Image (cartoon, each protein chain N blue to C red):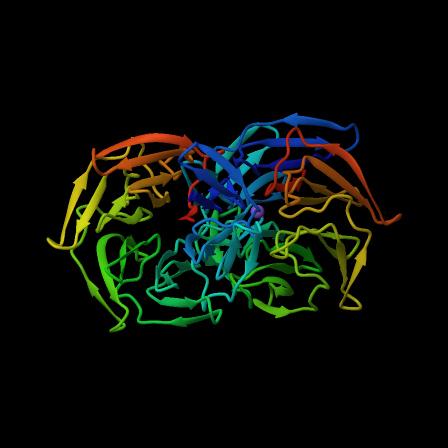
Length: 285
Length: 285
Ligand code: NA
């Protein structure tokens, strides 16, 4: 009975919400708020614990980029602070390999990071690894074949269709085949041995198009588009299906949750979040 | 029969309101809207004309920092554009010396300005002067003894308790005694030869504390606090009393207007604005 957790987000200002959706019965739980309101963060799970990584506190009286790492225990309904990252990372990408959290790119004020760091929960320590070949904020991250893929984003000048792959054993990055579409703030996940990149911003419009990377052919192929165009959407995989949560369509902050069935190549609206928001962190446990 | 004018502000989005309060009879006038919505702007008066300087248009369709200078004539109820500043300046500080407008600090996207520029209404021209020693956004500005004081703010990393002074004849800045409290977005004004810094934000809390700088002793002393904590408040002096307008208390956008009587060292609520808002520009004419 795993749940889809959504942490933080943005609607007029950064949000503290921690909510959990049950795809089986369609119910939503209201869990303990984040200690600091954050948008542009990422979520991940290690050993049944939910982690909220980086982001930014956007408030009417001023803004603060976050280097924070916070851990939520579903059994206790409590958030606990962890060691912070070396730098603040807003619009961060995150992936997990062997119980270690990789924090990828993101921004700190005018700085667009190419730097990458890894967290060890057993030691509560962060350590820098090899930086990416490109500076990437609003970057999508996917773990596939024990490699860490960094997809699209924004380098400070241009939104990107480029993508690269990290080899943990060799501690190095290599560029892979570029996507068909330029995407910053896309939802990036892994489903049935393929990397999916859904929505995002091409530098002009928020996108509803969805493409998938097949490792064997090293090609990106378009699949069925989402019903709603969205950037800064949350994404996850639950029981062989992709779930996209909220986002921004250029005018509205979406409460829509769409579900992709790979067997039928179709998207359907499954639920609505309690309120519209973009820039959430999402994970399943 | 001078009026307290409040221009722009923020509530869900940047506002276009121009309203004028009469402290003698408690009435509010609804004047011509600003041509462009703006929050984080500053207001000032030169030769009976009201000026709206800098700010930002925060809308659901995007955010744009403003380099605009607009002039309102109370006799015609008309806004007229003036020459723009060299750069956009959101959360700007403004002061007037010898009929010249000084535009101090503020932000442009991720940039935190230390730059300062001066407007000459007779020539409709802006010119840069010596930059401040510190980058300051959400900076409070006060003119005292023909010197321009820049108080607190945010440098891009930390909210500040520091303050500095500009010498127009020498074209140079000098650091002065730091405040007792770190304050960004405080209300800063001059009353009876003292600089007052009321409220503000420290990165964690909105403040109700008020302190005053005495030039002779070069010391900051706390006076009676305001009834409501507020950051990004509007401030002005009218007939020997300080008026604080709106702001943000960490939850609500205030419509509250408080008045400080220096003879009794007491604050009282005198009126309410027609709607709650933060980040207004305020001036008296
Ligand atoms: Na907030």
